[PDB]
Image (cartoon, rainbow, N blue to C red):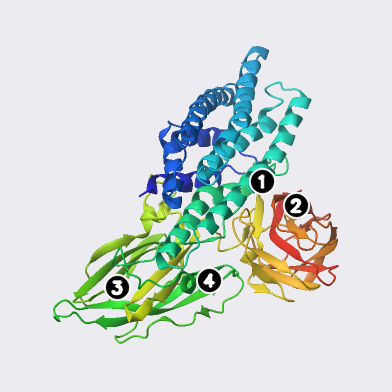
Amino acid sequence: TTKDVIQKGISVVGDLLGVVGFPFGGALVSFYTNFLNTIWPSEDPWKAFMEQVEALMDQKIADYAKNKALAELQGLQNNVEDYVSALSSWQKNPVSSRNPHSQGRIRELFSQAESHFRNSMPSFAISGYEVLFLTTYAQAANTHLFLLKDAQIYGEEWGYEKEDIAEFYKRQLKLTQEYTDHCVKWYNVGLDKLRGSSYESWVNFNRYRREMTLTVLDLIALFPLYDVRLYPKEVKTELTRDVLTDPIVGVNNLRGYGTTFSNIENYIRKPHLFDYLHRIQFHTRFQPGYYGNDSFNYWSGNYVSTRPSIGSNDIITSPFYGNKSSEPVQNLEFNGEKVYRAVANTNLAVWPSAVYSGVTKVEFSQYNDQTDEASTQTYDSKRNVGAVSWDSIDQLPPETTDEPLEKGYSHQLNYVMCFLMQGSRGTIPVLTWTHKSVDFFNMIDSKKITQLPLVKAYKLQSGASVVAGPRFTGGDIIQCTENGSAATIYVTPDVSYSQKYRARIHYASTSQITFTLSLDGAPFNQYYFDKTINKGDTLTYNSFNLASFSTPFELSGNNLQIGVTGLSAGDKVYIDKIEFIPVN
């Protein structure tokens, strides 16, 4: 269920990834038409977003609050549609038909929509219903901000006063901070409300966390890229966060045998440098049926191996998860394959006073981007397989239903972990996924502004570590506590000739610091950076600063090293991303 809103959520993010930064006119209009068909066609999507959170929270919005929200949304739809049709005409029509009379038409349509948004927003944030209105608020907030940036692109063409364009910009800055902070605050409120002790508590908790990531958190991560003044070119970026699909189980009710909340939550992957699925070792066990005829084999445990980010080749192998094999081990290798789907079979044996169930078969769909070919690899228990009961596509739909899956998928497999049920009743497998936008090569685009997340480094040093992200950056961050080197990231230049770049850094610091940049161990850039926070402070939107390095440089190597100095006892520096600006 709810796959509809999940798909809409996934698609919007996927489309926006193509019109982020300063977009070209044709691309902007194309986006807008899909946008209107997806998010703004009727009241149906809005109603579905409200029901989505009500389902996750097991609470309902007061009818009066639900109705007013829907009323505001009908009005906002008209404003958006009227605006888009006019914008479309403007782009299409030559720089001749632009008379003062048509300029005023577009100016008032724009002013109306923008104003209606500021006025309506509080309706999606009524006291006591903040969490329940989260996906609705996130989608409305996104529209408002996306709409706003248009004033910086077409402002002068439309004949707006310098004062008007400026007022719009300040308004965009204030709202980007507010809307972001609002979403993170209530996201967390909801998350804590779902913490429990049972296995059933954890499934709910994790479903909320995954669904809120796809529909809210991924979206707010794009907001800063709507600043076409700071980002006067197209932006190449990616989402580095993990999402965990629902556990694969044969029965709807485990009658108390499900792994406890703590035994799952405390053992799932902790903030780590980015990596890729490399290998899986399947362990199988025999489950006897009370009458022999009803027996079956099942996936009991596993090993997982991942390869790090480009620049390092040493394979990381996981501890053993679950139970040792009673049957012959099965190994699947993924070197240079992208797992875009996983479909599973489960089976059960009913005993006089017990039920035993397990995952008997798993079919993995893989795509080879090098040899441009799809194929499948499967795990088979080999004894009484049963039927398919779990499909990843239901939880992680494709970005587009237009293209074939191997082209339009939204996520790929990163991790596999087996949990043991209480009292030796079986094994629960849990799968971790990563977003399709992640570029393995860490490629620096010669025409765009490239955002490089620090978690794409292959080596941390001087006691630098991966820490949980503040929920609005699309992934995790790097914490620096000592003076010295911090991270080494491998970079792939897209051009051969001596193209020059400017670097910008998105960070947070308790003190004034010095950042140093090196290529293949040779320093080339060193600069002074401001303090952004006080010791102890929690990280909100304003905690981060985006600052340039003075001097331009060429990519005469691949190994980029970031180093920090100027720290004192108790000082901390958080690094999110490094950006490259193609310059002449």
Q: Which mark is residue 546?
A: 2
At 56% across and 34% down in the image, what residue appears? 123
Amino acid found under the numbered disc labelled 3: Gly
Q: Count neighbours of disc 3 (C-alpha within 10 A) and say few if under 14, some if 14 to 19, many if 20 or more.
A: many
Q: Secondary structure under badge 3?
A: strand
At 32% across and 69% down in the image, what residue appears? 255
Q: Count neighbours of disc 4 (C-alpha within 10 A) and say few if under 14, some if 14 to 19, many if 20 or more.
A: few
| Residue identified by numbered label 4 | 269
In front: label 1 or label 3: 3
| Residue identified by numbered label 3 | 358
In front: label 1 or label 4: 4
The vertical placement of 159 against 257, above or below, is above
Query: Of marks 3 and 4, which one's residue comes earlier in the chain?
Result: 4
Q: Secondary structure under badge 1?
A: helix
Query: Of marks 1 and 2, which one's residue comes earlier in the chain?
Result: 1
Amino acid found under the numbered disc labelled 1: Pro
**Spatial CA span between label 3 and label 2:** 50 Å
| Residue identified by numbered label 1 | 224
Name the spot of residue 160 as percent of width and height, x first.
72, 22
344 to the left or right of 430: left
Amino acid found under the numbered disc labelled 2: Leu
